[PDB]
Image: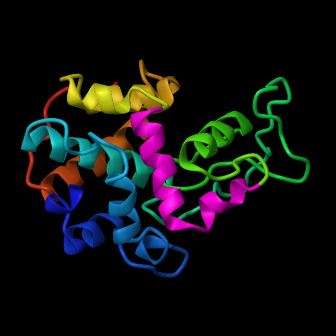
Amino acid sequence: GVGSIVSSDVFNSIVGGAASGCAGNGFYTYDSFISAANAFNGFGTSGSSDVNKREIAAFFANAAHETGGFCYIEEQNPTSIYCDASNTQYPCASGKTYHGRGPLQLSWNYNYGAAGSYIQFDGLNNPEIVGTDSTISFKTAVWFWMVNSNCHTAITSGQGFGATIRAINSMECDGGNAATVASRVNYYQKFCQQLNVDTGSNLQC
């Protein structure tokens, strides 16, 4: 399992410790990550050692970007509750909010609903659990990576780190946001060095 690639010390060196204004590994804990990772067959384990290390680095690099370096659990100063009232499969619960939570900043009624179906929490009535239970929190991210997006297939099929950016937020690609692409890439290069793996090519999108 992923615990043969990521030791406690390497995890802490990727996520950081709790500090002023920064949740770090106070919320984003090592055994919550491992517990989550090992629940999704293939995550960090499908390919060669190098491919698996790149996958892990790519996951953490996007998560570090989305969370401000693992400082935040929830989207900061949201202006929206992220309720798409047109979605009748996953209707919004009055009084609940669907702004970003967890490593990959799960957002919208429809995504919380789908994630909760898969992971076994009530995403519509209890989206806030993604910000209070670290194992669920990490599971939402690994679900997004493995089930709800092309991230896993991209990084494990030769497409490069940039293709994981495209799978998470394609508006940043094609010139859309050079700065956010640079931030994601900078974390990926750091984490590949910490995991002792070549970054590969095609880092931008």
Query: Residue 80 in the image: x percent, y percent?
Result: 79, 44
Q: Residue at x 9, y 47 (%)?
A: 197
Query: Residue 113 in the image: x percent, y percent?
Result: 68, 40
Q: Examine the structure image and report whether residue 135 is included in the region drawn in magenta.
A: yes
Whether residue 204 is visible, yes or no, is no
**What stretch of residues is rendered in magenta?**
126-147
Whether residue 16 is visible, yes or no, is yes
Occupied quadrant, residue 46: top left
* Apparent side of residue 125 relative to residue 56 in the rendered image (left or right): right
* Apparent side of residue 185 relative to residue 118 in the rendered image (left or right): left
Query: Residue 106 in the image: x percent, y percent?
Result: 59, 45
**Which quadrant holds the C terminus?**
top left
Query: Residue 82 in the image: x percent, y percent?
Result: 76, 40
Is 154 rendered above or below residue 185? above
Q: Residue at x 55, y 41 (%)?
A: 118
**Which quadrant holds the N terminus?**
bottom left
| Front in this rendered view, residue 50 or 79 | 50
| Front in this rendered view, residue 177 or 99 | 99
Is 37 rendered above or below residue 155? below
Circle count: 0
* Apparent side of residue 148 relative to residue 87 in the rendered image (left or right): left
Occupied quadrant, residue 147: top left
Q: Residue at x 14, y 60 (%)?
A: 4
Please tell me whether the stretch drawn in magenta is mainly helix, strand or loop: helix
Q: Examine the structure image and report whether residue 102 is included in the region drawn in magenta.
A: no
Is 12 rendered above or below residue 189? below
